Image (spheres, rainbow, N blue to C red):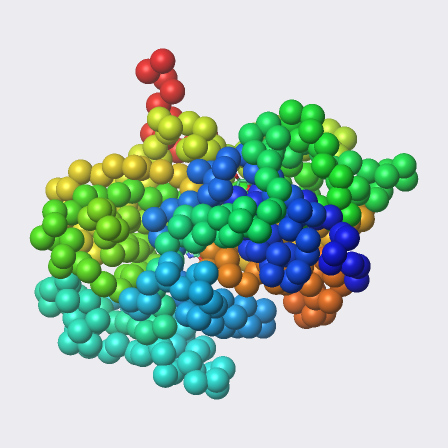
Length: 436
Ligand SMILES: Cc1cc2nc3c(=O)[nH]c(=O)nc-3n(C[C@H](O)[C@H](O)[C@H](O)COP(=O)(O)OP(=O)(O)OC[C@H]3O[C@@H](n4cnc5c(N)ncnc54)[C@H](O)[C@@H]3O)c2cc1C
């Protein structure tokens, strides 16, 4: 515990999901706005954030105990918090499959919700027939959904990810939070007291020093490139592309639920401009490089994001074009011949157990790690920062702290993905620098 009036906190990655949430909650908790500094490479929402997207799925996670609480806190805020409400489109979500194994997995998912005995059945509906699926998704045809079975999350939908992070940044700026970007916002190293162990701020790549009582490293997929996380977090890329619908087609897809099949991927209702985003589903791609983060004695093998923001001409691997097109054929057969654009790789960071890594650095007192999003944490935007502030103040619940603790040793490359990510170096087609 410490004064909220006199304590300075610097948040690194303030343009991102966990960083923005943290900044927001320092301000809501009553920290002096001018004592809060938010740093990022790019002005918020950072072009580089995994959160800078037309959309992310809003759904429920149950694996661990924290999952359930986090998921319910999240939903409550997206539904009722004035700041967040406009960016949650509660169109529901259909999780479907037509394979023997995929359907059994869905029945398992449903059983799981039911087994919790907190009334999840009232917002999660089993869809056993074509009729029930067609009712949730009128764009589908009966022939198309032959043998499909479904779980419908009536509570679910999608999140206007970039807009929501932007709204936080506006709020913070208004309150008088300090910001640093580019050279003045790019983390280089922590600064230490004379003991070499107590963190007292951080220095950026342009040499600017920021002194503060607590530092929060919420740099997302770049976090393990900035400090040695001992393989707890492996950054991986997922992929998406866009297709343009005509005004007529776009009208038809208005308010369609998010549609997801673990064997294919998912798509979202068109944005205001008639554009649908399609994603596949796969274990992600790594991009290992020899890299020496601050504090490391020798260079390490770290998956270093290949950022679309830095490399506008990058697309994604040829293997992704195949799987994206398979998703389109499955979900949007009438659009098979639409041309794709904005082919993009977007980066997240996996831990071995898919839980967050939110904890004080084991050696550097006052330096908090807040990462390990594991590719399903955008929905935690509204609430995750509350628990980061709790950690900062020493009041984080023991079960939550334990789940998120420093815990080197697992296999983050495989995580809970069913397979280790393949490396971009082995997956041709994404790099186009070489017309230059
Ligand atoms: C294709 C794809 C689809 C996804 N779909 C969903 C979904 O449907 N539902 C869901 O809940 N989640 C989804 N996710 C995951 C979600 O986007 C992430 O879990 C979440 O955005 C992670 O937030 P973060 O704070 O950990 O990182 P980020 O949001 O990426 O923010 C990290 C910030 O750190 C900054 N940074 C990097 N280096 C430095 C530095 N040196 N100094 C200062 N700042 C730095 C970056 O610019 C960035 O702004 C998806 C992810 C991907 C890739």
